Amino acid sequence: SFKYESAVQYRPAPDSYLNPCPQAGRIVKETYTGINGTKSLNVYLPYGYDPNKKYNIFYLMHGGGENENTIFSNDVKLQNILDHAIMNGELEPLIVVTPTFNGGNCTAQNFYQEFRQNVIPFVESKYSTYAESTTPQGIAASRMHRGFGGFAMGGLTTWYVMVNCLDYVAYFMPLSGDYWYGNSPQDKANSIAEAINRSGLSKREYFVFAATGSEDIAYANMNPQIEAMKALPHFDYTSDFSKGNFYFLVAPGATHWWGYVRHYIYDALPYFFHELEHHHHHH
Ligand SMILES: COc1cc(/C=C/C(=O)O)ccc1O
């Protein structure tokens, strides 16, 4: 059913999507040991999950003061939105992982290292993504079907993941957080451009769908960064990812709160993972 729009507008999921869906994906609490010690995450598997099929995977980071359980807690209930959207055909089934930047030496800034070395191999060796194996080569070869996003400090995590993990991840969803690398917006954009240059990727091989609220403090620093990025040849601004690769959704009146941010995921996540996808779809 999904069709790309060129300037998608903010629309909250219906209130009914916040209540439990009978077609509920399974949420599995996992514990693993990596460079930052023994840590946990949650894995959302779509309803009907079949390990002999291959699923898109989206990693989603919490904000400051939160943890790996926040996004699927009663304070957010993202799984209800996912369940309803997948059941209604709005969102193709995918795996959603909620890790944490807490623990050991880990920070929102440096999480990408643990992500690369420990999180991807742990999750993707257990569950069925497009990664045929979880060697660096197997992960890189499946990058078009892997995404990363996050809220606030988790948005910062997302930007650091982008600049350090373009080889492994093609889709990025920074929510209400800017990239802290640089003394000006131009420095931030230039850093991203340099990462893209180093990666060798074409503009059809990475995608950024940023979002925030018009009354969300993150707008103050996101907006200048987005404008600087728009000026780069590396980005073609439009939400139609069949045509371009960069969009910034600003929700009128929304404030810095998961109550709103969950809806940004509802609006944006359906836009991910169709470019170079393996099914024959018309979007
Ligand atoms: C990474 O960018 C941002 C982070 C925050 C974090 C707020 C908090 O932890 O309370 C707020 C605005 C931002 O633009």
Image (cartoon, grey):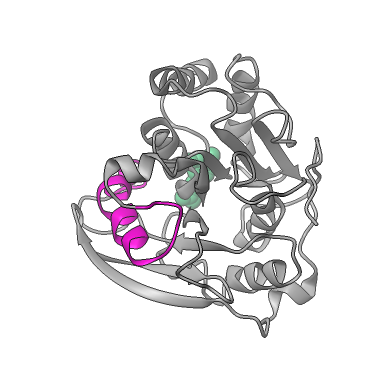
Front residue of 114/217: it is: 114
At a point 45% along the width and 41% down the height, the residue shown is: 143
Residue 142 image position (x, y, % from top left): 44, 44
Indicate the quadrant containing the N terminus: top left, top right, bottom left or bottom right.
bottom right
Residue 193 image position (x, y, % from top left): 48, 19
Q: Overall secondary structure of the magenta stretch?
A: helix
At a point 26% along the width and 50% down the height, the residue shown is: 106
Front residue of 84/73: it is: 84
Image label count = 0
Q: Is residue 191 magenta?
A: no
Q: Please, which residue is most extreme toward the bottom here? A: 22
Q: Taking 149 as reference, is 217 left or right?
A: right
Rendered view: 232 above or below 144 = above
Rendered view: 44 above or below 222 = below
Rendered view: 171 above or below 79 = above
Residue 278 appears anywhere in the view: yes
Front residue of 13/146: it is: 146
At a point 37% along the width and 52% down the height, the residue shown is: 132
Task: Read off the magenta span.
Answer: 107-132
Residue 177 appears anywhere in the view: no
Residue 58 image position (x, y, % from top left): 50, 54
Q: Quadrant of residue 78?
A: bottom right
At a point 38% along the width and 39% down the height, the residue shown is: 140
Q: Taking 4 as reference, is 172 left or right?
A: left
Indicate the quadrant containing the C terminus: top left, top right, bottom left or bottom right.
top right
Q: Quadrant of residue 227?
A: top right
Residue 236 image position (x, y, % from top left): 67, 23
Q: Is residue 117 magenta?
A: yes
Q: Taking 218 as reference, is 1 left or right?
A: right
